Amino acid sequence: AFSVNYDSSFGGYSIHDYLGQWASTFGDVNHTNGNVTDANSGGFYGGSLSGSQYAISSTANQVTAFVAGGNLTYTLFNEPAHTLYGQLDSLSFGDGLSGGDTSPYSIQVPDVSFGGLNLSSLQAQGHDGVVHQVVYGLMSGDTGALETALNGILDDYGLSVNSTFDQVAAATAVGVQH
């Protein structure tokens, strides 16, 4: 049940191509946004360290954000030690998070997102566990780990992170490659 959760308007990017564009704005410290009021940084939702959701906004400009969500667990007292693992299904890139009070973080300007990954890492999947990878990648403005995770569903149909927002969604819809 995977798909690209892009705002139905950008449906013509190669996944890796738009994600790079997201990181473009992410890296730029002076990048503001007139649509961004609150601009919440993140730091989980249903947990102090482990839980459901894990959002991150650009440490540079603290607008260009990323909402992660799955079934997380922070291994402080655990085996890998001070690491991340657990499940992952959906990402969500966009400018400026809001909420983070009584509601979960959500992008004020909701852009491309991800859903249906269904990737869960085992206990000892410390920094090598793709969920840990993708999150800290995202946090740093890297999509080079997410692209490889994305390839997990795409490769089943024969696509990749370089597949278009139309083709990915269509292939995960049913597959329209023939």
Image (cartoon, rainbow, N blue to C red):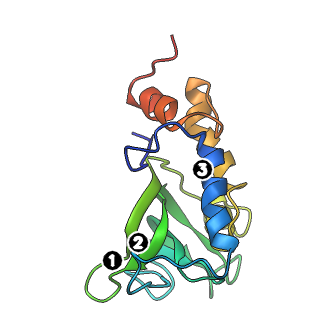
Looking at the rendered structure, the kind of residue marked 2 is Ser
Taking the view exactly as shown, the residue that stands out farthest to the left is 102
Front residue of this view, candidates 119 and 75: 119
Front residue of this view, candidates 9 and 119: 9
Question: Would residue 23 appear left or right of 88 to someone viewing this image?
Answer: right
Q: In the image, residue 177 lies at what x, y percent?
A: 52, 16
Q: Are marks 1 and 2 in contact (CB under 8 Å)?
A: yes
User: How many angstroms separate mark 1 from mark 3 (CA)?
Assistant: 25 Å
Q: Earlier in the sequence, mark 1 or mark 3?
A: 3
Q: Earlier in the sequence, mark 1 or mark 2?
A: 2
Front residue of this view, candidates 55 and 36: 36
User: How many angstroms separate mark 1 from mark 2 (CA)?
Assistant: 10 Å
Instruction: Write down the residue under mark 3.
Output: 18
Using the image, determine if residue 118 lies above or below residue 127.
above
Instruction: Write down the residue under mark 2.
Output: 52
User: How many angstroms separate mark 3 from mark 2 (CA)?
Assistant: 26 Å
Q: Quadrant of the N terminus?
A: top left
Name the residue rendered at 60%, 61% in the picture: 22
